[PDB]
Structure formats: C-alpha cells, structure tokens
Image 1 (cartoon, each protein chain N blue to C red):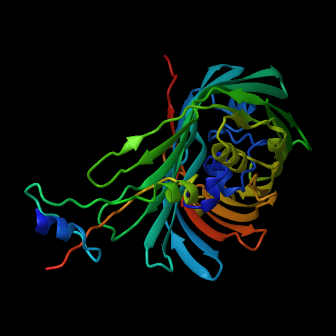
Image 2: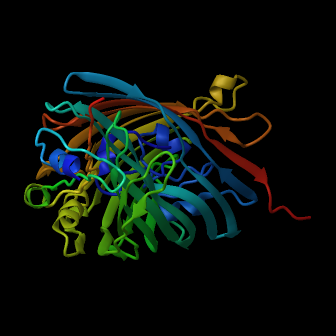
Image 3: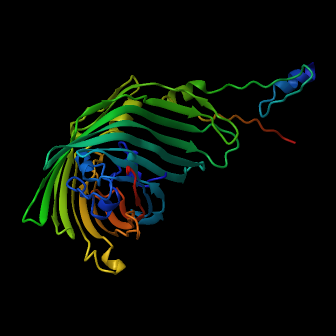
Length: 53
Length: 406
C-alpha cells in the first residue's frame, strides 16, 4: 500500500498498475469544443495515450 | 456523365438539350418552319402532315464530342458520347399524321475535385459531383384544317432525377468519418406543346413556309430531398439522415417563330427565333434550415434564354447519274444566351457553326445524316470557364413501304 500511495503522488507521469492498483483519469475539454466548433459536423475526435519503455 | 462534362450544369436543370433531328442539327437548328417530308421533326407538331402516303419513318441518333475546357491558366479536355433521339411517324388519313418518340430535355454531368493541405499539416480532399437529368416521352398528332394550314400538339410524359453531391475526405488518416450531402430532385409530371404552320405558293415553283410554336407555363410534381451521409467508406454504407422538403419547380412559357424559303425542290433556306421566359418562374423551397434554403435559392435561379439560328440545304441535279448529285449538302450557324445566372449577373454566351450531309441509300428512301458542329461558350466574368466543344453526329431515317394493300 505505501508504494502504491507513493507512486500515485508522482506528477511527471501516470501509471496503469493493473491488479487493483492504479488507473489514470483524463479531463476532456468538452466546453471548449462546444464553444469553438458550434455549427460544424465533427468527423473525428482522436485521443492518444503514449508510454515509456 | 453520359451527355456533358461542363461544370455549368451544377446550376438549374443542367443544360437544355436541343431535340434537333438529323437535318436540323446540320442546319443550325432551324426546326420551326421546316416541312422536309423525308425526315421527322418533333420540334413543331404541325410538321407531321408532310409525310408520304404509304410510308413509315423510324429515326434515331448518336453523337460523339470533345470538350476543350479552359480557365485561370489551366487547360484540359474531356470526351463523352450520347443518345439524342428516337421517334416513329406514320399517316392516319389523307389529312392527319401521328408520331411517338423518346427525347432528352436536359442533362447534368460534372466531376470537379480538389486536394489541399493546411498549415498544421492536415491533408484534405474535396469532391463535387453530379448526375442525372430530365427526359421526355411524347405522343403527338398534326392535322390539316385548310389546304395551306396545319396545326398539331404533343402530349408528353416528363420525368427525371438530378443528383448533386459534396464530399470531404482526408487521405492518409487512419480512421475517420467522411461527410457527404447528396441533394436529389425526382420529377414526374406532364408537358404540353402546341404548333402551327402555313405554306404559301410563291412564283409557281418556289414556296415559303412560316411556323410558330408555344408551350405554357407549368408547375411540376416532385420529390425534393436533402440527404446527408456520414461515415461511408470502401467497406461501410455509413448512416443517412434524410430530410424531405416542400419544393416548387416550374417550366416557363416558351415562344418560337421562323420561316423557310424553298426553290425547285433543290434549295431551302430559313431562320428561327425563340425565347423562354425563365426569369418569370417562381422556384423556391420552405424549410427551417438556412443552409439548405440558401443552396436551393442559389442553384435554382435563371435568366431568359434566347436563341437565333440560320441554315440551308442544297441538293444539286438529283436526276443525273452521279452519287454526289444525290447528296444533300447542309450548313448553319446559331447564337444563344444560356439561362445561367451565377452570382447576380448572367453567366455565359455561346456561338456555333454547323455543317453536314444527307447520304441516301440507293434503291431505298432511307437517309444517313452524318453532321458536325463547333460550339464555343464564353464566360462573361473573370472567374468562369470557357469551352470549345466539337461533335460528330450519326443518324438514320429508316423508311419503308408499310401501309400498302392490294
């Protein structure tokens, strides 16, 4: 538990430790899309997560 | 894309096809005053009464073309081929004749594409296409009310489908949804056409004819629809968000008049004039969506079309034994202001010169009517294209002794 709680507090990166460990949470900019692209047809919205070795 | 590639056809019903048969196509289209009894003429119903007693005439036609298209320093050319008419004609009485046939009215064809790249690095491609047209199938009759005077009518079924698309594609992107809006207009109604002709016996050998033709203003049954497709691909159909609209379509009042002089059955000359009241038509659509409304009001808008044409044919010494004495020689030229309104101003202005032959089959009365036409369309404003179009035109008036009895 202490190691998991310590790794949750790192701020340069996020982890994905699977067996009931760590998830990562993302905040989408829905309000900005709703303001800037009103009247458009959305053809694609792409989100990418990428990792270290 | 079976009759045109001119990108002017993105406006209106396309460009109107002249249902000018073999003799008129070489003679500049002077079809109102003509009474050439060996070939069919649907453009003026009063012309049917000239047919010989025992005959049945079956005319058809093809045409090839090469459009040189130019604008903004770019030059390109495009080649299509068509089917321009098919019609039967026969006599019912010493004073009445009837015909039935199949004719084009207007056609559309254009593909105009584009490829781009934004400053952010995204490449994208657009594609604006169009297809279809309006067609006409008719039954008509003409009668002699006096020894000099004939009148007639054409009653026609009048149907078609014009489809016009806009696309937005992103080549190289892994997975995305393409946007395409396909506005379609199906039409199915009827059309009436009226005509009369009068012939005068000048100087005992010549004859002079005058003809007029008229068709009334009309409002068309239709099925206008505004489809937007989303997510279609090489593997999937996407989704279609259809939208059905209460659009109004019309045909204008049309007037035409002309004459033909004739001498010793060796020479004929004539000239025609016609005007179509397109600017006095109430096209429109009702909807809550301004984008659609603006498109309709900018794509279906017109100006008055007028046409001026002159032509002649000459048949020298048709009883002498030499085949070039049996060949009908034809010439003509014409001028038109097309009905296109682009921006607020009128779009184009066109000129044409025509020539052709009248090759007869020996030991028969069939005629092969090879003809050719050069036409130039000039854009009247700097942002529009110019066209130089060339076209051969094969057509055969079959003719056989049909209603004979012992």
